[PDB]
Image 1 (cartoon, rainbow over the protein chains, first blue to last red):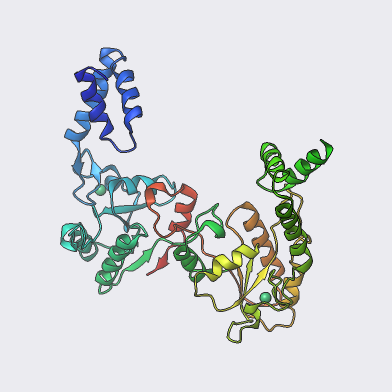
Image 2 (image 1 turned 30 degrees about the vertical axis):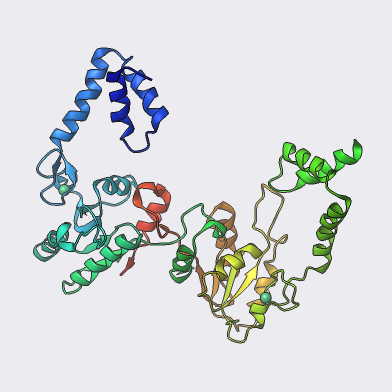
Length: 197
Length: 195
Ligand SMILES: [Zn+2]
Ligand SMILES: [Zn+2]
């Protein structure tokens, strides 16, 4: 057992996802063993990141400015909007180092259990961007779980009346996977979505 | 003991059995009741002597013509190519495929000791010789092996004019953008379908 001020660190660190007890203890001692200025850096980086967070006025992504870097990039293709559930999906998609389009961040999915409706996530503003803008394609890239799929599907009906091309990211068997260890639901999509040549 | 040493040799020849595991299995085995090791030994050869290969699809079942190829609706004009008998039960568990199969028993891996005549390719072409099949579905694994094998069977199948398709690569159901490898994600993106 540890002094209170250390128990307090350990407890605060253990609240973070993927940080168990032993891992928290370790980190606490490492931290309180770092030079005071290094621990000041950590501590301030934490507080400042939270304080400085803003949501882009165009796509709602996490940013520092009024309009995020991506939206203000002009040789980036504003006629294609990749719709995503969360800020960190934008990073995942952005790391695919193809894709010159822009983004729309919903901040969630439709979810009757969580009690989240379409009016509780950034859907209407997606509509408005498509209504008021010159949009060639909306790529629905929510997750392929039930709610990500319900959400992409809700959005798709909505955008129908506009004459936009709306696509959904390919479900299937992941690269490097094997048929044996693939759930039956994915096999089904892999088969059903098979493609020529 | 030379008899144990040979057991150990025979065991570690097998896939998934490392040197230590062969040895531990070897001792367990020589400790089993005689009638249990007889049974193990018997099961080994009996499965080799009784095994079949379907006359149409080359799957191992205990029928000369397997129950799928025999089934009257099953659609012989569409053939789903997989590597392994376990793959057939995988695909079947989806309670959705209508066509029939072609089991290769393996893939083409230079780095393992297997080539395009160590597996059941020529016999697949023969099925596609008379022009009576529409699509061959290529459903080898989306790994290195699987993919080689498939993009090749596909050249061979090019004549014959049949329609050849490939099991769709992408993000699996239940998966999420955060934990999907870039390669898979890039495929999910560049293969997106109009909803
Ligand atoms: Zn933005
Ligand atoms: Zn058969």
